[PDB]
Amino acid sequence: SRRWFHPNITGVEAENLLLTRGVDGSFLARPSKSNPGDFTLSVRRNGAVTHIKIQNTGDYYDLYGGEKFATLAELVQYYMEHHGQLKEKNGDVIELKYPLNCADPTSERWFHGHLSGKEAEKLLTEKGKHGSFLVRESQSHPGDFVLSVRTGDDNDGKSKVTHVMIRCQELKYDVGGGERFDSLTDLVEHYKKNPMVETLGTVLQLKQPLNTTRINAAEIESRVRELSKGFWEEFETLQQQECKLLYSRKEGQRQENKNKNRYKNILPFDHTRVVLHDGDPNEPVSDYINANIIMPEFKKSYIATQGCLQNTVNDFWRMVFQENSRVIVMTTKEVERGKSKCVKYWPDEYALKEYGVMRVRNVKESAAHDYTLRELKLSKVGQGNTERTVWQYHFRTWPDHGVPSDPGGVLDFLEEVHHKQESIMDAGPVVVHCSAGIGRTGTFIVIDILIDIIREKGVDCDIDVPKTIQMVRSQRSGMVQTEAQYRFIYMAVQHYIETLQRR
Ligand SMILES: NCCCc1cnc2c(-c3cccc(Cl)c3Cl)c[nH]c2c1
């Protein structure tokens, strides 16, 4: 449910909430109001509030005195299932026991605060189907709200929109009778499960929130102008839905696989992980790599993976070989900020190296402005005729923190990557990696998915950036990490539409 996240609370408001409405073990998370990528975990212990910083520069959530995580929900899940594991600077244990729930509705897909009654009928008439709903602030009754629902068959009167008035009396919400709820979310959840019935029998089913993020490609410029004037709010609504994505990650947690993960708690989902076959028969667990298949849904596929560790380079090449991948995208330098982000896993130019049962030749490197292309030949040792060329596109100019201030470089790169993949008959998924394999990796993959829709169907197709992101996030944890990456995706799509109108 992720109610412990408070999107619009101050540091002082957070202390007071925990001191007046919480107990020892109560906690909440909140953003830093002028520092995107900064979050705070506020926790009560010993009748006093402690504040722990979480930093995200684009690769992972880094909890001070704790671990690195793919999502705040995964971070809270981990500490609510492990006593004694979160520690103060001096080393005392901080326990997260009791989430302190937020009543703020602003990050709910169905909450459209500023929106009139006829404005809500238009949207539902056009964009909505049976069971589509939204909640808006009342115009005629200050402080109250309205629930607008479409029901019918999918202009002949077969459909209709019903309005239901939501009273706010003494910080509780009701539909005119029955139960009084502490938040609009509690109210909506209750009638989502126990639908209202009109006397004459219509069931006001709340099946899905009204979709307002799906846009036609030719109107990208206007939506971006609107989000610029916010990108923040839309992003936060997306992050709220990450509690629905806590799929199991058991294989990455096995003792045998511990040291195959760059970060112990950033792990591939079981249901999409790449399973490696034909492993050394002596090796107990030989089927594991920290990598997931990303299959775009609603025909190129990807594998999103971490930067190699020295002990997983053999597994990486087993995976490229097994999957028939012919194109690799590397999203970081080898070293950034003096720290190793992905080990060198390819031979020096003109050299040949064996990586366990795999053999790799570096045929030729070519320097471009923003990237290096390495033409590699991959084959299985002892088996001459298994040789294939693998083209490695190494993007070298992404800044150490944040995102590029212009998307042309990335877009020129993806264009060239796309033409290479398309030129090779029956090529397998495009491998995209480095660092933890969720931030830049997920950003490059999302842009690539969106740009391919526009390249095939033109500027007469519909795109939905957050839906696309949620679909990739259901296949690997935390794909697209920051609000800066989120804005960068919109800017890249826009830029790609502006140069297609230049043709
Ligand atoms: N309270 C803001 C209401 C406007 C709104 C609606 N919808 C989304 C979405 C979204 C869209 C499709 C699917 C999913 Cl799962 C999401 Cl989160 C992400 N930001 C949004 C913002």
Image: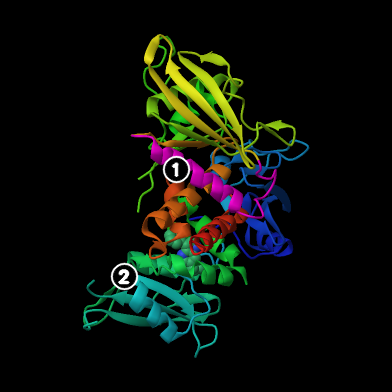
Label for residue 131? 2
Question: Does the magenta segment cover residue 72?
Answer: no
- Mark 2–mark 1 Cα distance, whole angstroms, equals 42 Å
Q: Which mark, residue 419?
A: 1
Query: In terms of depth relative to the viewer, which is nearer, 116 or 85?
Result: 116
Give, as a three-letter code, the residue at label 1: His
The residue most toward the right is: 90
Which residue is nearer to you in this view: 321 or 197?
321
Left of 20 or right of it: where is 154?
left
Across and down, in percent, residue 24 comes to 65, 50
Q: Nearer the viewer, mark 2 or mark 1?
A: 1
Colour logic: rainbow
**Residue in the image at 42% along x and 9% along y:** 282
Q: Toward which corner of the image does residue 420 lie, by quadrant? A: top left
Question: Along the polypeptide, which appears first: circle 2 or circle 1?
Answer: 2
Chain part drawn in magenta: 397-425
